[PDB]
Image (tube, coloured by chain):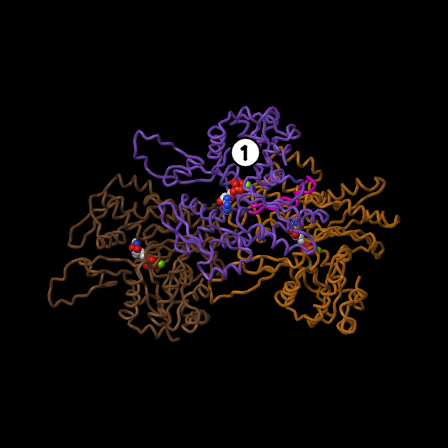
Chain colours: A purple, B brown, C orange
Amino acid sequence: ETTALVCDNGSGLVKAGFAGDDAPRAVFPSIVGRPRHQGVMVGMGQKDSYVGDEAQSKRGILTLKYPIEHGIITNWDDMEKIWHHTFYNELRVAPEEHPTLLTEAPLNPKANREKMTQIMFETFNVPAMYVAIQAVLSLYASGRTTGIVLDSGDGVTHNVPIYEGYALPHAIMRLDLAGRDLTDYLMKILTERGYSFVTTAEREIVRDIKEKLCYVALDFENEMATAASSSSLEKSYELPDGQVITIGNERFRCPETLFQPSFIGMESAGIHETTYNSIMKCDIDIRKDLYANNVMSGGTTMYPGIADRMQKEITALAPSTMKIKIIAPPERKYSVWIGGSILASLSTFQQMWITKQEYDEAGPSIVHRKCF
Amino acid sequence: ETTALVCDNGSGLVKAGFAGDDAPRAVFPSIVGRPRHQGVMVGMGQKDSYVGDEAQSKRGILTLKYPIEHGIITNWDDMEKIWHHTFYNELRVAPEEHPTLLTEAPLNPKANREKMTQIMFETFNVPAMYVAIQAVLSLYASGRTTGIVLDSGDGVTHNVPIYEGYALPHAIMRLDLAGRDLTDYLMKILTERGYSFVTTAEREIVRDIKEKLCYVALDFENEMATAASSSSLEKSYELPDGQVITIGNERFRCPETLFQPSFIGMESAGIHETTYNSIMKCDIDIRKDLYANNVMSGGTTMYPGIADRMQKEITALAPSTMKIKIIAPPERKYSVWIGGSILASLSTFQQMWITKQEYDEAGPSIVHRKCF
Amino acid sequence: ETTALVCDNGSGLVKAGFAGDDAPRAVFPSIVGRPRHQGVMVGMGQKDSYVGDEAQSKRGILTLKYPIEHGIITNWDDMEKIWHHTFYNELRVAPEEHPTLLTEAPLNPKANREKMTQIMFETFNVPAMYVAIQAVLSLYASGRTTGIVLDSGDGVTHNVPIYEGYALPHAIMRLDLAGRDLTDYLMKILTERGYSFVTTAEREIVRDIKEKLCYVALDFENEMATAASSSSLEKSYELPDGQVITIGNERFRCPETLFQPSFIGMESAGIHETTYNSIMKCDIDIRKDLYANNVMSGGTTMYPGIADRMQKEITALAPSTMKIKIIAPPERKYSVWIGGSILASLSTFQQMWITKQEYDEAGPSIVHRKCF
Ligand SMILES: Nc1ncnc2c1ncn2[C@@H]1O[C@H](COP(=O)(O)OP(=O)(O)O)[C@@H](O)[C@H]1O
Ligand SMILES: Nc1ncnc2c1ncn2[C@@H]1O[C@H](COP(=O)(O)OP(=O)(O)O)[C@@H](O)[C@H]1O
Ligand SMILES: Nc1ncnc2c1ncn2[C@@H]1O[C@H](COP(=O)(O)OP(=O)(O)O)[C@@H](O)[C@H]1O
Ligand SMILES: [Mg+2]
Ligand SMILES: [Mg+2]
Ligand SMILES: [Mg+2]
């Protein structure tokens, strides 16, 4: 083949393009939007459903659904609209000509991967495809064969240890807390300063407040004290319609949910303890190299101060005699897709695709014997 | 102390009285009103503002302002008249004599609770006070350590799950739709039958139409079909001055907004879906006992048929494997205040009051470190 | 004494009672749990810690901690709550009056036995005590003085060869895989069918799924092929909250971790290989009588088909010239406690107790010269 696609069919935001390009060709919301009002205009070019940037643009008149929840596809009829849009609108390919690398979280339901395999061969007729783990792809972008990858998206956070190119699948950790739960918690805490955000259109406004204003405080109790000497840490922000809102300790109490999942009431260890537990499930000789190669990936790792905070916290859990080093590159917003564009381009990978001629004799069950 | 005051400082309607009474000593409109017409009579007892039953009585000559919107005090200069009137006129006690229990919605703005705290210690000089969640009080009145309380007053509808007396604040739900929004919708749909209601006093006339004649259908499409065999479900009502109006399917299409908020153009779950979502956000082992102890509170839960409609709808959402039971007691019009009268009476509660001596060294910020 | 106590302080299930009784007087979860939510009701039995069935019953609002991990007590402040509950709450004895037989896995830390001795004399003031090896007690319940015992609890699996009443301590094997690791692996593989169990309360739901439905395949590859021609091996389970989960090959792929520890990623012999390797470490003349007396003990030996599988596999490793018999009694769930109740009742054992008079001139290091 001369060109494959790589599609990072993620929660909240899809990244899409071709193998061997250095960054995604297309990046848009993993959203389908549907009207919630009467179509009172006549001769208007009214469309029954909107997807990606069209839905994000028109959202005052729409109800917005993400067809992926926690890295699991929950609405296949609208997920087919996202893949149809992806290929025919801004990639503008013929899917029958290009083999597609697809992307998934570890410890997902098998039925997700099977129906995703079925749609690619039976609805899009692709030549071939493969499903790769987001955290395995994240080491190709880094240029490594050992590291522990913390990947944190819109839906799921997960840790995957790799040493000398072998995964330790028994030491993988998954966590149903990422960019959506932080946005919902930001909506909840913004209520107590007097602002209301509740519609699926207002959750997108609060996602922009989260992306623009929020950060990870290197010591939470000292930052909560600092914010009581107020206006020192406060930022103003301008809503659609031009009303201004101001934010204080909620600017960093929001991202702290990653380190203290008890803020959203769940009983699980923080992302620091989860990375440390994942290294401690690994065999003793590999732990020293995993601590030094603690890779970060995905948009929920983009906060200011989060690499510093997690270096402070893994260094408090690990023994003091060795170098915890956290590798947070500036393109980590796309390092899954970038690593998929490398893998789909490798000359040795071209024998590993599931081909149409191998699917159609074995059914969607083929994807469990041929993929990790 | 020998007695304590207790107030549900309600949206639309205040309830007030003393600890250990089995019902409120006073219940009256949460209203202040000012003249909108000339005082032409010389030697008249002319007065520049009115409150409660006095404003409700003079409402031909007044414009009526509710100083509480959606459970938030939006007009302190008139809310201070409501609290002043409450203590000095129909409770007729000196506020410095008795500590006050006070009442709030969950997820409210912190500035509301702070300013309420300040006014009680600095305008009314009370010995001590506390602020309690309307739904936590409703389990004291119902005699339970566990339940999910749907509370629906004039201004707000909210759900609080409680199990073994511990609340789950991650699973709390709040909804800016209750008795006011149903009254505004009733003005709009009575206008489809040609009746005009637009002044604030006409909203009180339409509120009496709602309170006297409205009800919840067990199945809306069957009731809308039944109303096409007309004059069966329809009723007649007598206005002030003695004119009469006849009320059609708007008699049950009004309360159905609680189950279909899209009738008033907002994009949110109905009260059945939001109570189910609140149970489904809880820890799995507690859900069986929340379905069995679903408690109704506040005047917007007083419609005929609402318990039967909600038992039907929650039974359709929940798995059939277990017994949904909705506890709608007849005193649920006052169950918040009744629960406060129990809480203020308990010997083990008297250490939980914020005392004047504990406020004046910490300011109104004391309330967030002693209330829920 | 007229009665001693015997307390099999095992991982995650404590079995306790009097010497001379035929079964444990008390059996309960070896668990302590603490609230993880705000207590909003007051005038109530609010309690800062729950233990045993109180923790297991209220688990929907608790984080649950096991104070024993792999047969090692890791949290003594909660193990003292388990013994205090054992003695005062449902044995309802005064410990000062009764000598107590305690119990431990072989190849444990010496400090675990020392601190366990210290607490019994300095916190509970017992007249005397002893620490027995759980596999030596499994021969006492079995009514034989030669055999090899596969004991497998919640924390640890171990083999102890005994011939003519002498143990062969060079031939003891210990494996840090038993009922907890199988439960945790079932949480992992249930995720691949779409069910997330993640809290320490949901781990108890998965432990009940494991106990009710899981079984050991006689031939794993034949059973996997049988489950691929599906629906014949599937069963379903009703959760708390009344949602139903169906379970298929994960019903027997879970217990196969005992025969293939590489499923949880650990490098070791399976329980068949570890038992055979233990017989091979023994002196050649005893091996015939060890194969003829392969005793099984503890709850992780309770799966349907495990005796048939374990006999099938030892019979393939051992030479065909002689007969393997596996002795898996129907009471084997309590055979350590039953055998401890026999040992503590023997007239020949009453010289072997460590007495308070013999502890308080030697310190807790007495337990290394007087016990096993
Ligand atoms: N600069 C930023 N600060 C904070 N959050 C961000 C930033 N950029 C993106 N995000 C968040 O990252 C989440 C998804 O990013 P991504 O890694 O693409 O996840 P996914 O792989 O699930 O699509 C979104 O919820 C978005 O709000
Ligand atoms: N019989 C009734 N039918 C319908 N609505 C009622 C009835 N009685 C009271 N209400 C409504 O209940 C609302 C407030 O009741 P209440 O429970 O006191 O709320 P709050 O606690 O907010 O004061 C008012 O808007 C009123 O219209
Ligand atoms: N019928 C059963 N089938 C499978 N596992 C069981 C059964 N009964 C008990 N267990 C398991 O046995 C384990 C502990 O049993 P036990 O022998 O008391 O161990 P311990 O001595 O460590 O307390 C628990 O993890 C439980 O899940
Ligand atoms: Mg991602
Ligand atoms: Mg109320
Ligand atoms: Mg045991």
Name the amino acid, label 1. Cys
Q: Residue C316 or B77: which is nearer the viewer?
A: B77
Q: Which class describes the residues within 10 Å of circle 1: few (<14), some (14-19), or many (20+)? A: many
Which segment is the magenta one?
A157-175
- Please give left or right for residue C186 compared with residue B128 in the image: right
Question: Residue placed at 22% from the left, 57% from the top?
Answer: B63
Which quadrant holds residue B346? bottom left
Q: Is residue A129 above or below residue C214?
A: above
Q: Is residue A154 visible?
A: no
Quadrant of the frame with the C terminus of chain B: bottom left
Count of numbered badges drawn on the protein = 1
- Please give left or right for residue B302 compared with residue A90 in the image: left
Question: Residue placed at 60% from the left, 43% from the top?
Answer: C190
In the rendered image, the residue lying farthest to the right is C285
Q: Quadrant of ligand 2?
A: bottom left
Q: Is residue C235 visible?
A: yes
- Give the x, y percent position of residue C131: 75, 63
Pointer 1: what residue? A7
Q: Is residue A159 magenta?
A: yes
Q: Is residue B260 above or below residue A246?
A: above
- Give the x, y percent position of residue B209: 24, 52
Q: Is residue B89 magenta?
A: no
- Give the x, y percent position of residue C220: 69, 38
Quadrant of the frame with the N terminus of chain B: bottom left
Chain to which the residue tagged by mark 1 belongs: A
- Give the x, y percent position of residue B305: 34, 50
Q: Main secondary structure of the magenta part?
A: strand
